[PDB]
Amino acid sequence: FRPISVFREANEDESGFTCCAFSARERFLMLGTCTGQLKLYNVFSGQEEASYNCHNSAITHLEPSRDGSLLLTSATWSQPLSALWGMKSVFDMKHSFTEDHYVEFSKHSQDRVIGTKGDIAHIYDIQTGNKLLTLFNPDLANNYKRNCATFNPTDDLVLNDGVLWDVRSALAIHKFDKFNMNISGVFHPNGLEVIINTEIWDLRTFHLLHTVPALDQCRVVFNHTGTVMYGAMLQKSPFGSSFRTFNATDYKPIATIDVKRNIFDLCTDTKDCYLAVIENQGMDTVCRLYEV
């Protein structure tokens, strides 16, 4: 992790970057801010290229589509709480997700959006904007405090609130038991395992494959090849000052990095050359680009 670049939010005494993701153009990073702006920065020079007023409250999450034509954002106190933005020619809102506090694209083909509203998952069609499915089963709910619904790599399954849904039938097929209060889980990009806090479960058998205590209360980010996993532990920074890497095949530790500043967000480029981290000097955040 060699530092390659650093920059702060132009013309702000209190730099307010809150999240980041690489755009489909390699040299440019998208960043959300605590006042609801989306910014495009040249990640190497630090130049602010563009700003758009996406929301009137802090941006908590953003996801650019692979093709470069679309962006998801989520905010904190706004309506719509999340939105899908079209980026071609004249950036504007395409669809809005009124009370979804978190949103992601489908994985295999990015033709859908899945939103989370508390313990409820919503599935939307990109072309039409129509809400296709609402996924909630009161008998199976775990009520995870940081629930984030997600598709599996092939888009045929959903994990919401620790419950596995079959998308075609729109019905729950398994409930994973609750062993923490906050972390709801993600699919491994390998399509074989679900990672729910410290428990790694087999999707085929539902057996426990691994116990990984170091993942407790962590957000998990994979590199684009799915071979390295980054875990940043929740503690206005959401995370503390260090993050860990793990080998994504056996969950073994690789490294622990303490940047000595609390972390807001971290992300990888598609070629897996870099890790961009938002780090608080204070709020007064900077973005550091590290070469992995």
Image (tube, rainbow, N blue to C red):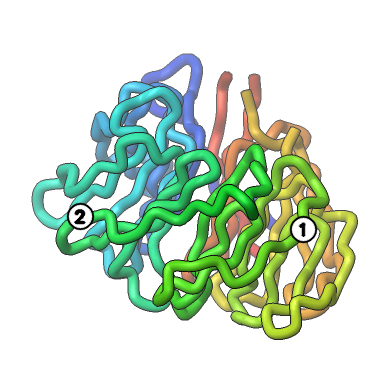
Outermost residue toward the bottom in this view: 204
Q: Secondary structure at mark 1?
A: loop
Q: Which mark is residue 177?
A: 1
Q: Residue at x 54, y 53 (%)?
A: 137
Q: Residue at x 54, y 72 (%)?
A: 224
Q: Secondary structure at mark 2?
A: loop
Residue 154 in the image, given as x and y percentages of width and height: 46, 80
Is residue 44 shown to the viewer in this render?
A: no
Q: Nearer the viewer, residue 145 or 17?
A: 145
Q: Which residue is mark 2?
A: 129
- Image quadrant occupied by the C terminus: bottom right
**Image position of 7 (left or right of 100):** right
Outermost residue toward the left in this view: 89
Is residue 91 shown to the viewer in this render?
A: yes
Q: Is residue 262 above or below residue 248?
A: above
Query: Callout 1: 10 Å neighbours few (<14), some, many (20+)?
Result: few
- Image quadrant occupied by the N terminus: bottom right
Q: Is residue 170 above or below residue 93?
A: below
Q: Nearer the viewer, residue 214 or 97?
A: 97
User: In the figure, residue 261 lies in which quadrant?
Assistant: top right
Q: Which mark is residue 277?
A: none
Going by the numbered disc 1, the residue's amino acid type is Asp
User: In the figure, residue 78 lies in which quadrant?
Assistant: top left
**Image position of 138 (left or right of 220):** left
Residue 9 in the image, given as x and y percentages of width and height: 43, 29
Q: Residue at x 75, y 49 (%)?
A: 243
Kindly check if marks 2 and 1 are in contact, taking CB atoms under 8 A apart as contact: no
Q: Residue at x 55, y 33 (%)?
A: 286
Please name which of the two marks, 2 or 1, marks the residue nearer to the observer: 1
